[PDB]
Image 1 (cartoon, helix red, strand yellow):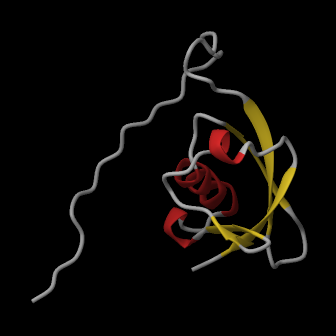
Image 2 (image 1 turned 120 degrees about the vertical axis):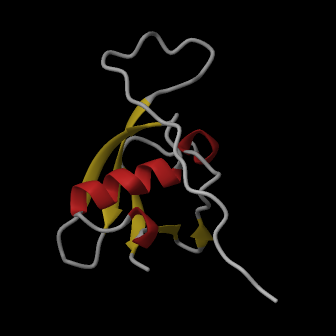
Length: 100
């Protein structure tokens, strides 16, 4: 008695030229994914994009799998339901990049 998986669908889309960040806060901040390759990895994202969305990019930038990217800070685990707006991530925040 056991299963796995549920559904597979996405609902995202990027719009060129921020159409005014009214109500829905969407600020741009640079993140630094500290990899274990030696060289750091920076990426551009907005607070509107959650860790998941971010991870996706990272995996897109690095080439890894969005499902193979873990963002940790000191001793804090980042969920896929917590955005940057919650972590108040600052433009240039160094986070521990880890691969599953």
